[PDB]
Length: 281
Ligand SMILES: [Mg+2]
Image (tube, rainbow, N blue to C red):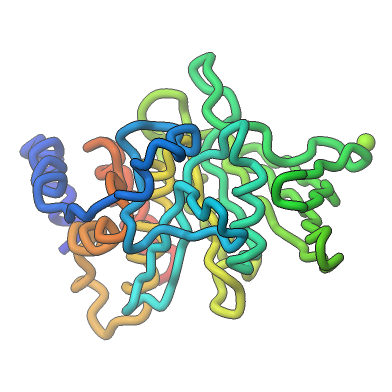
């Protein structure tokens, strides 16, 4: 039903109409904590906030706030943390969350600079011998290795809790070719990227939830988890054509607002799922 509904929406040119109905139907829950004045500099955008009921709380709790949401997909048996690109003042918070939530992978879907503006702070070290220390959260981060491919980069990082001297290996998956405007021409490299993340074990239930971000953490980030969850459901169910991507998206939007930012991102999500299903038989 998905591939035929796709072609009929293309034929009738009603992607904006379909997308607006999702916007209208989407849940609205309070974001009281995000809106407190003391957290203004912990939010990149005024209009992108985590719901109180699903927000990630920092454990070092004098201020527990971070702009990050837990998206828990019950039937698919997969969880994701969606967050904004770290700000100059929230890089220590970002790695604290990674530590406290026991995540193994970080998925980054933007470049640090896009359209000539800073979209995210440089929150990981660029050279092995120049490690980063986050003094506010008492964490040390070391670049262990880096593998640059044409459409993405994988980095091995070592995160040390300086308080307890425990260390963990974090895998950083950086998709580096999403265009400044619009969506990719073809989903092929995005899907290959998704399967690289999968193959690493970072999405497996023995670990904490993968941390996924772009600049706002709703657009490309929404595309990534939406495609992943829909493909899992097609694999699991007796009837793969029963998977309704609009229903899955609305379910995810119960946990973080704004996921999928444009009708073009919606269309691209359909395209990724349809093409990805062909790969997984
Ligand atoms: Mg060197």
